[PDB]
Length: 52
Length: 62
Image 1: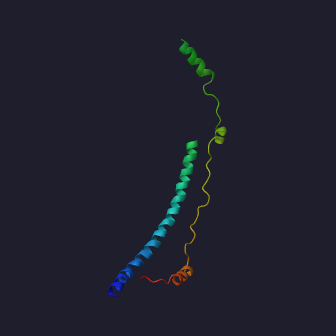
Image 2: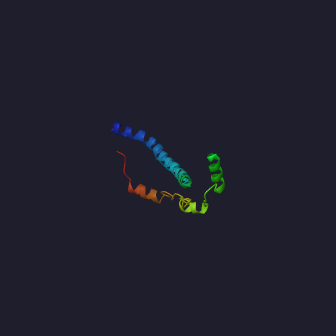
Image 3: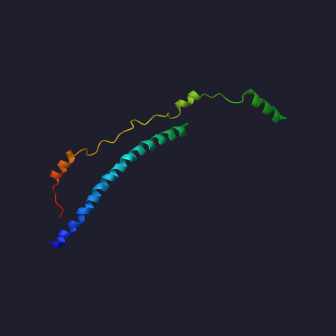
C-alpha cells in the first residue's frame, strides 16, 4: 500500500508545475500570432517588389 | 568613319524608345494589404469550463 501511496506523493507537487507551464506556453503562442501577421505583410511586399 | 556615322545617327535620331509607367502597373502584381489585425479568441474563458471539468473528470490518479 505504501508503494502505491509514494507515486502519488511526488505527482501531487510536480503536476501543479506542468499545469501552470502548459498555460504559460499557450500565452507565448498568442504573441507568436503577432509575428505571423508581420511575416505575411513582408512576404506580400517582397513579392510585389519582385514583380516590379 | 562609319563608326562616327553610326554613332551620330543612332544617338541623335532616337536615344530612348518610348516607355510608360502606367502601362507597367497592369503587368505587375499590385500591393494589397493583409486583412484584419486579428485578436485571438479568449480561450477557455472563466470557470464555466473549470466547473464543467471538475465535474466531468473527477477521475482519480491511480
